[PDB]
Length: 161
Length: 159
Ligand SMILES: [Cl-]
Ligand SMILES: [Cl-]
Image (cartoon, rainbow over all chains, first blue to last red):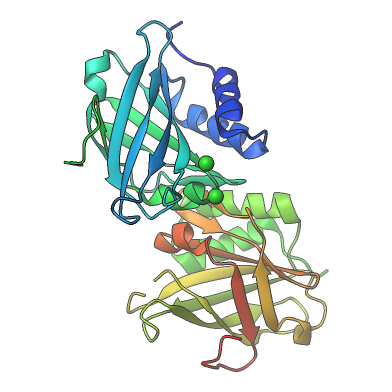
């Protein structure tokens, strides 16, 4: 009862990405089939312009069913999908969040976890027992599956380590 | 009696890529679901070290059931590069006359598919459809390339 269903997730993504494209449902249906039901999700925006495409700074909100909601910031290497001045949107599924404070830290990518279908892509990052699945669209769908590192923080920071 | 089966292409995929990676069986399925039965496949190798990753030069063989097997070369952009180069398996759809294979192929937007270390996208020239399948780094990066020229003899010129 602390988990989200694929249907709730597909709806949040349809609304956040402004897309009814079948790729969103396909990618969500793939993440759940591989990892089960998340107990949180992050909607936010990323931009890489400050480091001219090579570092991504993101900002969004963590949504849970009974642990409240929280501003979340993140930093990582970028290929420039978010090099657009308005940045680009990302929805991350969060699995196994037991306590909000355990969310912050450094996430290591899982090799061969890239998945792309119909203009929607994700990969998998893990820290301790938390799995993180950043779902991106468009350019980010294809380029974001190359990030193997993401840091999550409670406050915005320039420092990605 | 001209098209290949999904199982046929998968076994060719396992053998050429040297992998029983389930992503091979998974990618070929999606290409067969989206596109049906191809009547050719190209096995070959790529390299972008001469243009430092700025341009790929490829070489292989197109295999058919009746038209014979024909040396094939391709040129296109690259995202980079290793010394040995990297392997590719190209599904060919709607290949009537071998001579209609050669020329410039334009990518299909949003056609990229990537699963378990395997990936393709789709490019087209007239009614022929080309699906270049790669593994590893090429699975992720190759799906960004939306141009390929196929030719009967090698050339430095990509246009
Ligand atoms: Cl976006
Ligand atoms: Cl885009």
